[PDB]
Amino acid sequence: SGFRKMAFPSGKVEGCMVQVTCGTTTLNGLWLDDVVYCPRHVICTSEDMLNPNYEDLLIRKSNHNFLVQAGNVQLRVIGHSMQNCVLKLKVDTANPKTPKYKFVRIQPGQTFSVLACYNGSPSGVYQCAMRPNFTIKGSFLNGSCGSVGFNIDYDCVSFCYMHHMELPTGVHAGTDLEGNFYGPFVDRQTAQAAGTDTTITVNVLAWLYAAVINGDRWFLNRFTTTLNDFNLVAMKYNYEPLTQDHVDILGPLSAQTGIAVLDMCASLKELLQNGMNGRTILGSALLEDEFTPFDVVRQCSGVT
Amino acid sequence: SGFRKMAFPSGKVEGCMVQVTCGTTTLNGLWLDDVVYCPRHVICTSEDMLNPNYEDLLIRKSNHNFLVQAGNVQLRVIGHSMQNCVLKLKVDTANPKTPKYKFVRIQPGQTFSVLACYNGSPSGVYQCAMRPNFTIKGSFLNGSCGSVGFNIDYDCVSFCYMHHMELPTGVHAGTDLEGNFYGPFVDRQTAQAAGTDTTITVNVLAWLYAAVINGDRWFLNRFTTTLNDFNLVAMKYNYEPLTQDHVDILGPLSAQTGIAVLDMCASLKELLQNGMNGRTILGSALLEDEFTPFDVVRQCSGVT
Ligand SMILES: O=C(c1cc(=O)[nH]c2ccccc12)N1CCN(c2ccccc2F)CC1
Ligand SMILES: O=C(c1cc(=O)[nH]c2ccccc12)N1CCN(c2ccccc2F)CC1
């Protein structure tokens, strides 16, 4: 019993973290095989940050200008190239700690673990969700760029995120491991609009199922609703519309608890319209949306 | 910017997790040097669980009855002994992945990371606080016993907790790495009273300082209070009394923010007496107490 915001064990990713220095800027790199991946803004100066011409800036850089250090050993850079907003630094040594890995572009609403790093060294690990507006509510300081987000499937690490930026609003933006930003964000020190961030309904429902499995059942009511009636309430409260796909993914949790999805939707409807009245659910006084139905099943069944 | 419930990177601890089987029971063990540490209730049968005579049960067990497996390789047990509620299984091979480590008995109110494990394999990592009533609000299932709690100081892992039990109330109990239970708990399947759990005031204040540093300043008021006046409010709301030591530890956060500790106490007093009025602080609708002043400074300064 118990329900926590659980991150994946970070060991396989710690063995990939390196420090990348270019000129006077230092950030984090991800060493997989003979390649180090890092944000391309490592080549910027504090003058270039407002609107950098990365192609021009990279042209003034040679392999010897990229200092890559893993622990205390220097890696020799034999190639460099820009792929979207990431630089791929080819090194002469394959990382002996390279785990079985994939590069995946996650969907909004999906979750992942972040290993925050500074100077190539891991400082902490936390669980995040890619918001519907493609930002993440992380915890990042100067030098955190190049820290990665990931998921683990037994022995395989799926890298989904690389940290690039913090918007003036305190929210975080970044790319997949091919350098494509999640959302409309660009890697330049400018004010950028993060759109309206909605609540991930399927995750709030999955977390209501986790609450039911872990003893918290006060919010359960004698009501039911329809997809269309529930969605009228979800629209008013800036919640993602629930689809039949979402109902289907909630199927295992519905079967385990014996509470139909639309019955849980009716409980959520009343929680939105009436609030919590000073009560809590799984130790929280608000509706949590950073646990997918997969996260709930995994935490409530103990998948290692 | 940003503030998350951040766990330590778990790699150094993952390299220590083993599976320990005795008879038909399997749980987790911690392999450091040539010793595997695990809960002694690994030697219990489902008949023994209500009141086991561990000394008698251990006497019917020999080295060959303890099956220790690290990954897929079997370790050879050359010695066994009970130290309080843990068994120390001497193996013929020192763990090549043994990190620099210490065994520490943490204080109530202090925090630590848990690497939840099943069958010697890590499933997840989360941050916990040792409650003033010596329980932890973890996330643990069958087979999770032997999972450890820890802190890291650069390269040194301080092991502070080993998971043993879940009380009928859904809260968790366990020992330090010498087998001494935190609290009055005993390792037997009986109803055990977890005392009244108070709120860790110094941590709630540290988290109010984290909120101020991260833009959330709505709760700041034009008031001040005294230690004795604040403590009259802390008593009424089941909060730990604030001491001058707590004020001193809050010193760096007070200096960084320019808000005196007693001024922050006055804000907390009003938050307790008036509630949140539907607002949030660092994304939470309740007062968070699982971040020590050290955790706040570390997360807000980026210590790796
Ligand atoms: O390391 C950071 C940073 C990241 C973060 O998430 N939070 C912070 C909080 C306080 C100070 C700095 C940061 N940055 C340097 C590189 N920055 C950059 C972006 C685009 C183009 C050039 C650039 F140099 C983004 C900012
Ligand atoms: O693995 C667990 C367990 C631990 C947990 O924290 N949560 C659970 C939730 C559901 C089912 C089991 C658990 N237990 C087996 C060993 N138990 C035990 C304690 C004292 C004496 C003998 C014993 F066998 C404690 C219970």
Image (cartoon, coloured by chain):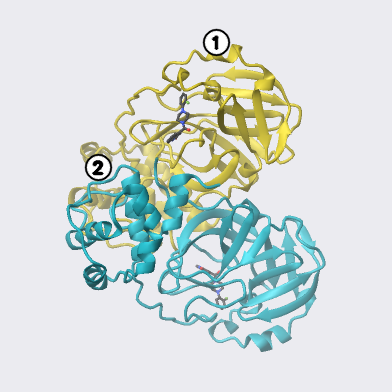
Chain colours: A yellow, B cyan
Residue A273: x, y in percent? Answer: 18, 48
**Disc number for residue A230:** 2
Residue receiving disc 1: A56
**Amino acid bearing label 1:** Asp
Residue B61: x, y in percent? Answer: 74, 81
Q: Is residue A16 visible?
A: yes
Image quarter in which the N terminus of chain A is found? bottom left
Residue at horizontal 26 percent and vertical 46 percent from the top: B217
Marked residue chain, label 1: A
- Callout count: 2
Q: Is residue B15 left or right of residue B235?
A: right
Residue at horizontal 66 percent and vertical 19 percent from the top: A80
Q: Secondary structure at mark 2?
A: helix
Q: Say whether mark 1 is within 8 Å of ligand 1.
A: no
Q: Is residue B59 left or right of residue A237?
A: right
Rounded to the nearest angstrom, the CA distance separating label 1 from label 2 is 53 Å
Ligand 1 quadrant in view: top left
Residue A256: x, y in percent? Answer: 43, 57
Indicate whether A254 appears above or below B163.
above
Residue at horizontal 46 percent and vertical 45 percent from the top: B301
Asked where in the image residue A90 lies, by quadrant, the reply is top right
**Amino acid bearing label 2:** Phe
Marked residue chain, label 2: A
Nearest the camera: B67 or B198? Answer: B198
Asked where in the image residue A189 lies, by quadrant, the reply is top left
Label 2 neighbour load within 10 Å: few <14, some 14-19, many 20+? some
Nearest the camera: B243 or A116? Answer: B243
